[PDB]
Length: 288
Ligand SMILES: Cn1c2ccccc2c2c3c(c4c5ccccc5n(CCC#N)c4c21)CNC3=O
Image 1 (cartoon, helix red, strand yellow):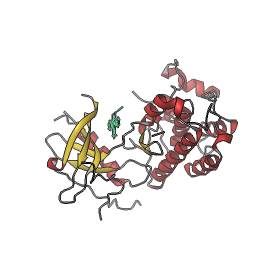
Image 2 (cartoon, helix red, strand yellow):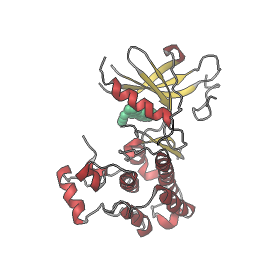
Image 3 (cartoon, helix red, strand yellow):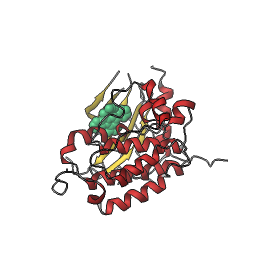
Image 4 (cartoon, helix red, strand yellow):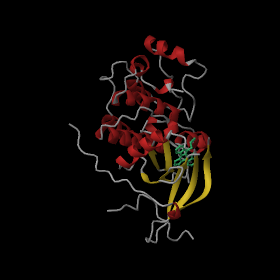
C-alpha cells in the first residue's frame, strides 16, 4: 500500500524564462537558459528541453513526472514544465556536463579525493531512490551530471539497451531491482577509476551475457587498490542478495574518502579543479 505522491508540479510561462544558448541539439534540443520567476527579483540558471506533435509527449511527460517527485541533494530536480505548443521541460543547470565527459577531459587533473567523493554522492543519490522505492534502471557515468567538480547529481531515473551496464539477471530475465542498480553502480565506479574508459570494449553485446556466466568481470583499473576493486567486484556477484546495499556503499567509500591516498594511487595526486547580481542557484531557491 503505497503513500500518495503529493509532489507539486509547476507550470511556467514562456515569458518567465529565456534561452541564452543551446547545450545540445537533436531531432529535442536543450538550451542553457535563465528563469526569472514572476515578481521575485531572482534569476535562476536552467536547462530547457524542447521537442520539435510528436506524440512522444507521453515519454517526456512521464520523465517530468518522475523528476518532480524526487528531492535530494544528489538527485537532479525538475523546476517546472511549460505547456507550449511544443512542451518544454525546465530543470536545474549543471554547467560542467555529464561526469563521463568531465572525467575524460580532465583525467590528467583529477585527484583521488574527487573520485572517492563522487562515488559517495552517487551512492547517496541511489540510496535516496531506494528510499523512494524508485529503481533507476540506467545508472552510468553519462547519467551523472556535474553541478560543480565538488557536487554531482544522478539523472535519467525516469525511463539501444545498455547491456554493458546491466546486471546479469536483467540481461537474461528483464529483471530490474535496486540490487541490479548496485551492479550498474559498480560499472559506473569502474568508469570513473578508468577515467572514462569503455567497459568490455571491442566485445559484442551478445557475447557479454555468457562472459558473465563464466565468471569473467571488468579488469582492475591501475589506480585502484584491491580494497576499492574488491568493492566493485562485490557489486558484480550473480546472487543479488550477496551484492552490497547502497547504504553500505556510502559507508565504505566515506571511510576511504578520509584517507584517499591509501585507496587510490594516482601520479602526482597531491598537486592536482575549477547582470549576474540576482543570480541564485536552484538549490537555494525553494518555494513553500
Ligand atoms: C548535453 N548536455 C549538457 C552539456 C553541458 C552541460 C549541460 C548539459 C546538459 C544538461 C542536460 C541535458 C539533457 C537533458 C535531457 C536530455 C539531454 C540532455 N543533454 C544532452 C544529452 C547528451 N549528451 C543535456 C545536457 C540537462 N541539464 C544539463 O545541464
